[PDB]
Image (cartoon, coloured by chain):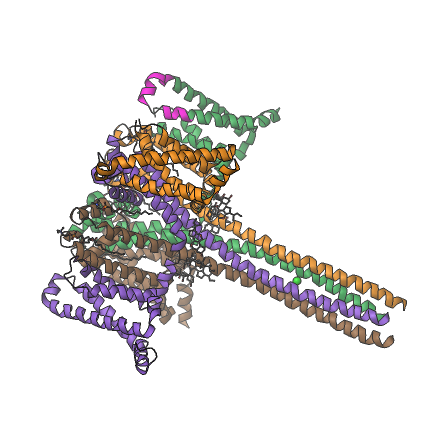
Chain colours: A brown, B green, C orange, D purple
Amino acid sequence: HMYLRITNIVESSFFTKFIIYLIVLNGITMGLETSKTFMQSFGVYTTLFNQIVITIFTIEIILRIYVHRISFFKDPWSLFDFFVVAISLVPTEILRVLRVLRLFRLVTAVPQMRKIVSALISVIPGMLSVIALMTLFFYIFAIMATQLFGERFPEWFGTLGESFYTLFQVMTLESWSMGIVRPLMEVYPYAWVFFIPFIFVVFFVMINLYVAIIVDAMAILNQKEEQHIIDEVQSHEDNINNEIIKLREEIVELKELIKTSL
Amino acid sequence: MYLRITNIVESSFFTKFIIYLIVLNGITMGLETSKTFMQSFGVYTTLFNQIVITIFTIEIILRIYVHRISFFKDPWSLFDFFVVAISLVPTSSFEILRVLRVLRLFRLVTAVPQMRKIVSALISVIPGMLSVIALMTLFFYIFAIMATQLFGERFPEWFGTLGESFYTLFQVMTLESWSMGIVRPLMEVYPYAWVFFIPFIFVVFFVMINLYVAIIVDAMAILNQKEEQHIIDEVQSHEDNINNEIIKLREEIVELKEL
Amino acid sequence: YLRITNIVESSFFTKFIIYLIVLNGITMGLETSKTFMQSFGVYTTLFNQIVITIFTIEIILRIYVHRISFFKDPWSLFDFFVVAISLVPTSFEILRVLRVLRLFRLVTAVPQMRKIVSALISVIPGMLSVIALMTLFFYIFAIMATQLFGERFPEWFGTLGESFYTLFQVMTLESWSMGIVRPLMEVYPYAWVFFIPFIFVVFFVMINLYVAIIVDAMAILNQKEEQHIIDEVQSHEDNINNEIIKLREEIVELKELIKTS
Amino acid sequence: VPRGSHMYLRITNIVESSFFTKFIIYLIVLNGITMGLETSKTFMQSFGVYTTLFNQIVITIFTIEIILRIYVHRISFFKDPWSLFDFFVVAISLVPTSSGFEILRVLRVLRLFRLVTAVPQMRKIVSALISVIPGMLSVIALMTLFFYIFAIMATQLFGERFPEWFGTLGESFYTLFQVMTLESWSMGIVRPLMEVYPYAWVFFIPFIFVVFFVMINLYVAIIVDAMAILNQKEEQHIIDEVQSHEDNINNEIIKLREEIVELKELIK
Ligand SMILES: [Cl-]
C-alpha cells in the first residue's frame, strides 16, 4: 500500500530531475576540486557537499531497490549506479580517484544518453569472436617478440607484458619505426620481417571487420525490405486470385441458368 | 526605382563582381606575407584593402536595404556581415582582429552556391551527433579529472591542470607520441599508467568509428524505406485499379445474369 | 598501311613491348647497386639505349596508325611524354630520375591495370568542389599561422609556403603536439585554439566526404533498382490491362448477342 | 596402405571422435600457457626441465595425430589448407632444436595458431576475412609497382647524402612504407631531407596522397560493389515474384476468356 505511495515518488519526474541536478552540481564540484587554489579556500564546503550528495545517492538507491526489488539488480544501469555509489562510500587511495566515476550516472539517469551507449555496445557481442582471435594473435607475437628481442632490448620486449604493451604501441603506429624497429635493426637487421606483417595483419582485420559490419548490416536491411515488398505482391496475388473465383463462378452461375434458357 | 537597385544587386554581374574582388583581395592577403614584397609594393596594398572594404560595406549595405530583415535571418549574410565589420574596426585595438580579418576569404564560400551547398551538406550531420559529442566531452572531462589527480603532481606539464589533462588527453586520442612521449614516462613513476590510457584509447576510437558506421547504416535504412514506400505504393495502385476493373466486370455479369 | 596496323594491334606487338617494360624494370632496379654498375654497368646502359629506341619505334608506329586519335588518348600521351623524357639528353639531372616513370607504362600497356586506375580515378571529379574548399581552408589558415607564428618560429611558419607545409603535417597528425604546438604554447599559450579547430575541421571534412560517397553511391543503386522493379510491375500492369479488354470486348460482344436472341 | 580395412576403420573412429578433437584442443591450450611461462626466467630456472619434456610430449602426440589424420583422409588431407598448416607447423617443431638457423625454435610458437584450425568458429572468422584478398591482388600489385617505382626514385635522389634511409633499394622501400604509416614522416625524414633538397616535399606529399587515396578508395569500392550485388540478389527475387504473378493472372484471365467464348459458342 505505502509501496505505491513512494513508488509514485521514486518514478516521478521530480525525483529523477532532482537527482540529475545533484549529479551535475557534484560534477562541477569535482572539477573545482582540481584547483589547488580552490581547495585552500572553499575546500571544506565541498567535502561536506560531497558527503551530502553521496548520502542522498544512498537514500535514492535504497528506495530504488525497495521499489524495484530484484529487478533492480537484473538491471545493468542500476548495478552501475549501485557500484559507483558504493565505491564512493568506502573510507577515504585509488578509490578516491574512481569516485569521479559517479559523473557517468549522468549517462545512466538520462535516457537520451542510455540510448547512445546501448546503440554503441550492440556491436560488441558479435565482435567477441574477432577480439579473441586478435588477442591470440597478440599473445603469440608477444611471446615471439620476447624470445627474439627481450635479450638485447629488455625495456621494450624483456617481459611478455612488455612485448604486449609494445606490440599494442606498434599497432597504434606510434614511433614504431624511428622509435622501435630502426633501433632493433641495428642489432637484428631482419626485424622488419616481424613487424611489417604484424602491422598488415592487424590493420587488415580491423578494417575488414568493420567493412563486414557495414555490408552485413546492409544485407539484413535489404531482407527486411525484400520481405515487406514480396509479402505485399503476395497479398495482392491472394486478393485478385480470390476475386477471380467470384468472377469465374459467375460464368458457372450465369452459364448454368443461361444454359437452360437456350 | 527600388527595382533598379534590387535588379542590380542580384544580377550575375553584381555577385560575379564581388566574387572578383574577393579573389583579388585574397591574393593581396597572400602577398602581404612577404617582407620583400611589402618593402616594395606595401603601401599600394593598404589602400587596395581599404578600398575593397569600402566596396564590401556598400555591398553589405545595399544587400541589407534590398533584403531588410531577411538579411539577418540568413546565416551566410550574417557571416558576410560579421566578417566585413571585423575589417572596419580600427586595426590598433586587440591585435587579434588584424588576423581574423583574413576570415573574409571564406566569403568566397558565401558568394558561390556550389560552395554553400558543400558546407551545408557537411553540416547536415552535426545535429544528430550532438548527443555523442556531449557523451565524448563528458568522457574526456571525467578522465581529465582522474588524470589530473593521478598524474598532475609528478607530471605538471601534462596533467598539472584540468585544462592540461584535457589537452594531453586529446593528444592521446590523436595517438601522437602517446607512448614514447607520455605513457612510457608516466610508467617510470606509476607502472600501472597503461591501465588508464589503453582503455581510454579503445573507448575513444570505438565511439568515433562506430558513430560513422551508424551514420552509414542508418542513412541506408532510410534509403531502403524511401524506396520501399515507392515500390509498395505502386503495387497498391496496381491492385485498386484491377479491383475497380474486376468490380466492374463482376458487376457486368450481374447485368447479363439478370437478362 | 594495313600491314603496320596488323602489327601494332597484334597481341605479339603489345605483349612484346610489355616484355621490354618488365625487363627494363629489373635492370632499372639493378642499376641501384653500386656493386652491379661497377661490373655490369656498361652492358645495362646499352640495354637502356636499346629499349628506348624500340619504344620510340613503337610510339612512332602507333602514331602513324592512329594519327590524331593517338594524341587524344591519355594512356598513349603518357607513353609519349614518358618515352620523350627518356630521350632528352641526361644533361640538371632531374630528368634522369623521371625516366623511371616509364615503368608506369606497365599500367598503360596492361588493360586490367588500366581498369583499376580508371575505377579509382573515377571518384575525383566530384571531389574537385571539396578539394577547392579544403585548399582554400588551408590557404586561409596558412596566412593566419604565418602572421601569428612566423616571427618567433621561422622554421615552421616564417613563410606562407612553410605554414602550408606545416599545416599539412598537422593534418597528418605527425608530431603535431610534442613537435609543434607545445613549443608554440611556450610563447603563445592560446595556440591550441588555432590548431585543435584546424584538426577537427580537416578530419571532419575528410571523413564525411567519404561517408557521402558511400551513401550517395548507395542511393543511386537504390534508384537504379526501383525503375527495374517498377518497370516490371508496370509491364505486369499493362499486359493485364489489355487482357481485360480482350475479356471486356468478348463480354460485350457476347452480352450484346444474347440480347438479340 | 590401409585403404578400407578393419584397422583403417579403427583409426577413423579415433580421428573423428569427440574425445580426439577435444583432447588435441586441450593440449594446444596447455602448451600455449606453457610457452607463456617459458618467457619467465624465474620459472625456467625452477620448472624448466618440466616444460621441455611437456613440449617434447605435446609435439609427439601432435605428430601422432597428424599421421592418423593422413591415414584417415589420404589426399583430401593435403587438398585441405587447414590440414596443411597443422602439418607445416608441426614439422617446424620437429626440426632439431639447435639447427643452423636457430630461429625455428621461435617459429615453433606458431603452432598456437593451431587453436584456430581446430575450432570451426575460428576457421569461419578467418575465412570471412580472407575472402576479400583475391579481388585486391590487382590493386595490391598496382601498389607494389608504385612503391618499387618510387623506391628507385628515392634511392637515386636521396641515398647518397642519406644512406641510412635511402642508400639501398631495400631501404627506400622500408622508409617509403614508414612514410605511408605517417610515422615521423616530416620531423623524422622529410624536414631533414629538405635541409639538403628543399623541394623534397614534391616527392613525398604526392606519395602520401596517392597511397592514401588508393587504400581508402579501394575499401569504398568493396563496400559499394559488395552492395550492388546485394541489390541484384534482391531485385531478382522481387522480379521473380512479380514475374510469376504475371504468369498466374495471365492464365487465369485466359482460362476465363475462353470460358466466355465457350458460352458464345453455345448461342452461335
Ligand atoms: Cl497484379
From the image, give the main secondary structure of the stretch colored magenta.
helix
Measured as percent of width and height from the top left, residue A47 is found at: 24, 54
> In the image, D180: left or right of B182?
right
Residue C89 figure quarter: top left
Q: How many marks?
A: 0
Q: Quadrant of residue A158?
A: bottom left
In this rendered view, identify the residue nearer to me: B18 or C33.
Answer: C33
Q: Is residue C59 left or right of residue A57?
A: right
Find residue C199 and report its horizontal and vertical position in percent.
Answer: 34, 41
Q: Is residue A243 found left or right of D145 in the rendered image?
A: right
> For the point 44% across and 20% down, which residue is it?
B51
Q: Quadrant of the N terminus of chain D?
A: bottom left
Vertical arrangement, residue A183 with respect to residue A95, above or below? above
What is the magenta range? B26-43
Q: Position of residue C68 (x, y in %)?
A: 51, 32
Residue D152 placement (x, y as % from top left): 29, 39
Whether A2 is drawn above or below B66: the answer is below
Q: Residue furthest right?
A: C260
- Quadrant in the rendering for residue A50: bottom left
Depth check, front residue: D187 or D252: D252
Kindly give the residue lying farthest to the left in the view shown: D45
* Residue C233 visible in the shown view: yes
